[PDB]
Amino acid sequence: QPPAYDED
Amino acid sequence: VSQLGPLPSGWEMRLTNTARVYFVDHNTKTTTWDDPRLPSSLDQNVPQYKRDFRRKVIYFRSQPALRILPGQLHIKVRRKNIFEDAYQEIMRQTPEDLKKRLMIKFDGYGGVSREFFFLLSHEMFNPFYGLFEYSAYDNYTIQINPNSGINPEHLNYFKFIGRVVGLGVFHRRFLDAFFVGALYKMMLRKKVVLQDMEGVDAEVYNSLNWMLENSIDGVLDLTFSADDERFGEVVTVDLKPDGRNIEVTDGNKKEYVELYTQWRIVDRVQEQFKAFMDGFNELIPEDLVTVFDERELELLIGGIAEIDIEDWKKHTDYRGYQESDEVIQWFWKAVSEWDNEQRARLLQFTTGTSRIPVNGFKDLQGSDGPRRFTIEKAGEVQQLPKSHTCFNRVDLPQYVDYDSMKQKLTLAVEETIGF
Amino acid sequence: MQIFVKTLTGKTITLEVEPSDTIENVKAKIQDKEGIPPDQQRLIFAGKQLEDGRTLSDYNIQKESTLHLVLRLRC
Image (cartoon, rainbow over all chains, first blue to last red; front, side):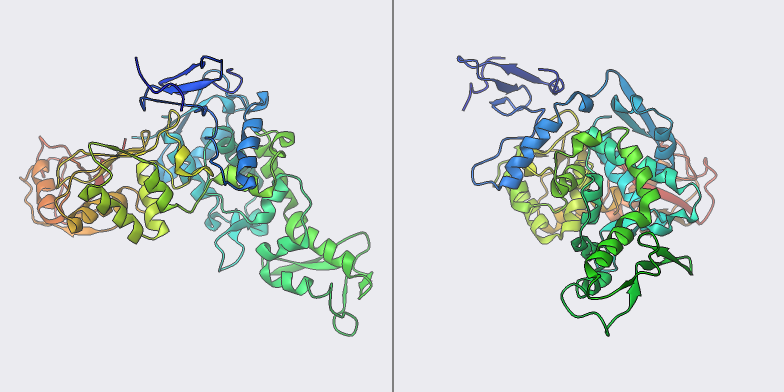
């Protein structure tokens, strides 16, 4: 898995 | 890398710590390796035909010839008039104009494209208009009706259809193309073999496949000529120069069989098909589509007609519901009970079309880009299920019981899209 | 008098109304027997699109007329 959705 | 087209709405593409491209779904609050502008990745244990298909799709989707042009194109049609309206709205645009984005408006956008193509293809490919004909009374696959020419302007309708079939390929839209296998071969300029006669004329097939192995002389007598039934009258044509004189025997069979096949299937509809590809080619360069074999082309044009319930269930997002609520469990129960047609009509209702990508529901397309089939908690019990064909979502109220839910769900699909 | 609502499928639904009855009052006559809420309902009489604030006599809807039912369930 890549960078899990975090900051926006 | 906008030679493959710009990203869908709400999508960002960043690099890993080692510059290995990955993507950001601002919609799903998630991230992935898959480019949303390209078919989804294949999971291990997947047939070569499928992996090789996703591969050729990218090849085909990168060439400059398959690149949307700047600006937009407007198609104004009325639903009850979709066929004759589309004809005008389209045959009046040049090929370049026809390559811009499609803004289709039914009288009285993006997700309208799916509903547009799915619906128009129903019309063109209906044996009603004499443009096509069901090969047999058994198989509901179609093929070019050789009697189409009773209508003098019939070669135009074909060019129009060819434009449209190509336009659906060009703008990533599926068609209710249930063609005979031999037609896709012709679309790839691949030679048609006697096997094709099966799907075309299942009768003449078994006959022709008998004079190749069995005996011939003293059993059947014929020449290099055939009989063309058109409108109650008949006309004998030479299968080759001076054919009605050159008899056929156990020493000819390879020839006749190889000349009849090429006549009944291909030549007999030379004009109709010539025009068709003339239109399909204004959009899809021949030397490009030929990256596919007859099967892949058929899939490219028309997607997967048969809905897989277990793949659909596995790739449905929920909003305001858990995967184990009474309504949801009930919903999937209705689906299980429903035949394919009843399912297709539900999909046609929610998404706008009953076609599905070869990658399955994993890669179900919306208007903007990737949009998984979605069921959301909304609306009251006495309220019909609603949909947003651009979002692939269905506001399913939390009905108190089964029999009452399966009721409102039905009249919603039966009345809105009463196929 | 009587009016016939023909859904997009041919389900003719015979009703009992008067020319005075409001369009709003028609869909409510349809709900009570078929389930579909008057909100979602959309009725068409001869190209027109019957509106709530009116009456069943405004759009010259005489007896044995025929309205077509439309269901706004799609975007």
